[PDB]
Image (tube, rainbow over all chains, first blue to last red; front, side):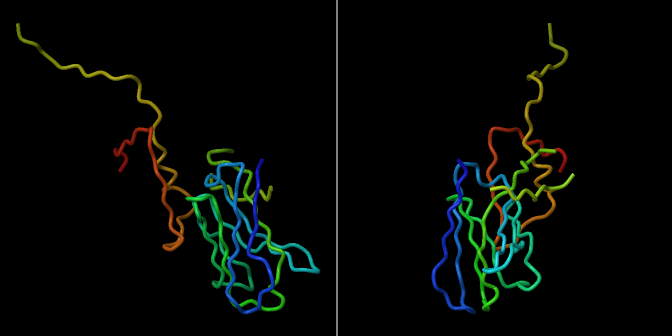
Length: 116
Length: 49
């Protein structure tokens, strides 16, 4: 039973610092890659960030260069994303998930697999 | 009688610890987003170093 709990919602002002927490359960956490996906309200779904198995930041989106932070609490099986300098349109229905591909399975580190 | 030569024995070399591809990974992480893990139950060679 893989499970991901998302927190960090509510009414928040744009331009302010924000903390989002996703808790992972039902699967060994720190052997998989992991993804945050942006989803503007009233619009579609787009990739915003990710991080490797080794807790390595994949990078940041086009409009958010060098001002978000993605980190991984390996101790309590959790993941955090901090945002800064929000605007009205950086609002998104952010999603948390992992990667299907296992360590030492099928070169290079596999990081795709938008799965759960 | 005196002995001649020494013999040292041990079973086949078992599961090595996978140091290699931890350092041959696509990349390392940041300083605040730094990485740590713990290894046990495996043999470490140190010979490749």
